[PDB]
Image (cartoon, rainbow over the protein chains, first blue to last red):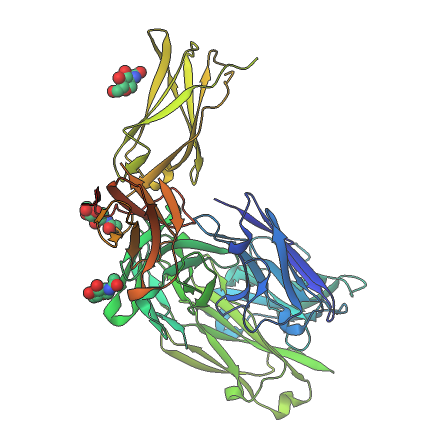
Length: 214
Length: 219
Length: 197
Ligand SMILES: *[C@@H]1O[C@H](CO)[C@@H](O)[C@H](O)[C@H]1NC(C)=O
Ligand SMILES: *[C@@H]1O[C@H](CO)[C@@H](O)[C@H](O)[C@H]1NC(C)=O
Ligand SMILES: *[C@@H]1O[C@H](CO)[C@@H](O)[C@H](O)[C@H]1NC(C)=O
């Protein structure tokens, strides 16, 4: 029951930046039995640093580890694009061995404006009784954004679902999809459907609307 | 050299049991311990327990004392984990790992690729593919809506794999129905809408469904 | 100020077999009406009992069992005269160990179980399991094990010395991530020392 808390939960750095992240234990941990792992989405965790400071095989020298007692740290001297991943700390000083909540390292870039598009429900889907309206926010940065659905200028709630991509390999941007699911009869009741998007790099919230007819 | 091959993705119903494997190669299976970890989506790793295949001796996390059963078969160099009284909370990706040395506390050096177990009363169902209209100067957006499918693995390509630029395939979202839904979009030059036929290829191997849908400017 | 510390003893002993019970008695001359037993370890807990008074001694018997891993750890006892609780100074610590959770090691004598007086005896405790340390008891010494040896064994040598006088020895294995969790006991080993003719 040695609880490992990692700070910060998420951070972003530019290429060439110095990165540092902390792992705090509720009880004292022997330095020989604190380990760091790097995990990228879809693959298994990889041993990165063993026994506080020693780098595992195949780990660049820009990485380093330090700490004792209750506080430990992982540091990157100059950020590289390959370094963007989630890093976990792990103690095996006392069983049960425990892992931290992880710290997600991302690549920081210049602000990018979201290209907003709106897609109406297909004719084939309307024939089956359900109506899905899709709003797309394409290639923006930073990740924080808000999508408000207005049906006949009426804000909606409980009928929307958002999905965000991970950072692009080239753009380092995100993209968001907000899908609104309504009944076919409920869809045919109201006229105008609009998607309102607010984000940095947009001077004012941008609205993309369409009329149910054509 | 050292490799850990875990069993494939498995779907199990609530209240039943599931058993997954972890096969070792490249080292004397008997000389080292084996650890099992649980990782729910978007969280850290939980240690389930450990087993020493030479003795088949075990040491379980108190949290998973009645949940998991760890066994080992030396003739096949394979470790097994059996989860009982399955809940939706037991849906996660489970890993097996071998430490650096025979000491079970040394760093978890080698890692299996993980087994994804989905626990749901939901129905194995093919996906419904609806077009996302270009809906007209510049670059337009166009996509496909892959809706109401289970289980999770779904594949989307464009023009049989000849359209890689501009594609964004969003992660699936779990609906209240218990079925999944994602959308794959792509930005294309507005001039090519009349010249080029853009189609999306969706594949859902669990239901053995393959769908090709033409996405065209239309009203 | 604060009352004196109670006495904490374990009957029948400090080493407990799995699924068995042990009685941790806590007694003192001060007329403590309440006794509190606290365990530090994997699953920390505090148990409360009321103390009986007999022959000017207040005491309470705590029943730890059936023995599990969560019940192993360091125990300390506290006494209190009042409730709603002015706890006394803590007792001397007792390390309650659960045994019998892993395969038993082998205990051997070098050069042999019986030697002439003055000849050296070294007890070797070995096992095919990767135990991190071994504990030798004569009816308690801990020595760390060594890496992969003959037959892949992990081993620890306990030299008895010139004037050991012998006895019956047992050996336990243990891992360093769980200090209070020991293996099955090795088979007893009678070490006899006879005089030189
Ligand atoms: C504790 O146990 C011992 C041994 O059985 C007994 O003699 C003693 O009276 C007990 N103390 C109590 C019951 O307070
Ligand atoms: C411990 O010893 C008992 C009795 O000799 C035996 O039944 C049990 O299987 C042993 N446990 C282990 C883990 O070796
Ligand atoms: C190694 O194992 C063999 C086969 O079990 C045994 O006969 C021999 O005594 C062992 N040697 C040791 C423990 O040194």
